Length: 154
Length: 154
Ligand SMILES: Nc1nc2c(ncn2[C@@H]2O[C@H](COP(=O)(O)OP(=O)(O)O)[C@@H](O)[C@H]2O)c(=O)[nH]1
Ligand SMILES: Nc1nc2c(ncn2[C@@H]2O[C@H](COP(=O)(O)OP(=O)(O)O)[C@@H](O)[C@H]2O)c(=O)[nH]1
Image (cartoon, rainbow over all chains, first blue to last red; front, top):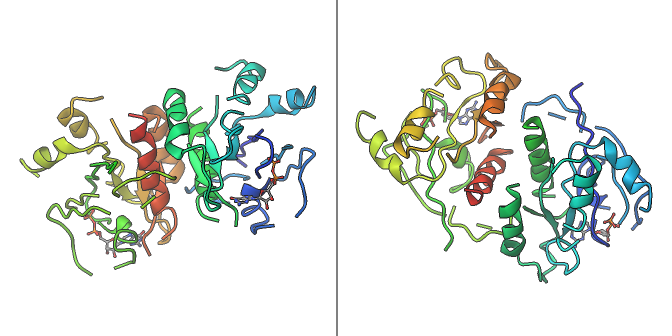
């Protein structure tokens, strides 16, 4: 089985849940984490489709060394969320690789966006590798299937 | 209006129609083309969402010079379809750019695939930029939204 041990680390209070509209495949109360992993589909590829982790003194710098995709997420709206890049360098520090990523911005149903989409998009244009999403279903597969896309290219 | 004058050129008898499950937004008899264009949504971006063209002595090498995305398609199954690369160089010859592309393979509902997905995937791994799809709805937005993705990066 062609598999893919990815992960996402993330900013303080936004969403386990994008993939919750997906492994288990619904929208769920319950705060997450510990490192709640689980394995589980076919663009024609044979994969085992995510290891969730909290919204880290040691431990973050432990369980992360066995990842091939930390395309973090934040709410595309929250004012310490892309701002929390702040989670990019340390993945580039753990697996000393200047790495399998994408800018996912959560939540554009609830109105307020300080983070104008096209604002974190210039952040994408230095990086080269963005997204907007919500479990309560579109676009979430999209992006982690997009994940599936650059790591074959890796 | 941030727009995107893309296009797709293509192999001999496969599908106008991926986007037909989309502009007009359904699955349609009717052979295509002439250069049947039409303009027409929001990952949070403001675009004008495709110029169809036939399944070319001059003319192909005419209307193509005003394109920013020819992520051709073929059926991921048909034995003169990725084989028809054969449509890659001439886009790299028109806009002398060694360019905004992706390997889209159509049709994996009807069984037979000679083109094993993971076969044209090594074709993707030289290229760096694949897909599998069907109008009769999933994945087609996916990929041309994926189109929307690399050309901001361009
Ligand atoms: N409005 C909105 N709520 C969402 C969306 N996706 C998930 N949720 C909510 O996200 C919340 C909190 O985040 P959590 O799951 O604890 O993530 P973490 O702290 O970053 O690990 C829960 O209240 C969910 O009900 C979304 O797209 N939109
Ligand atoms: N089985 C199948 N038929 C499709 C799919 N998408 C489109 N069609 C069919 O594609 C056919 C022929 O292609 P056409 O639209 O003429 O494309 P072009 O010659 O390459 O410009 C029509 O018979 C459609 O009904 C698909 O995903 N699966």
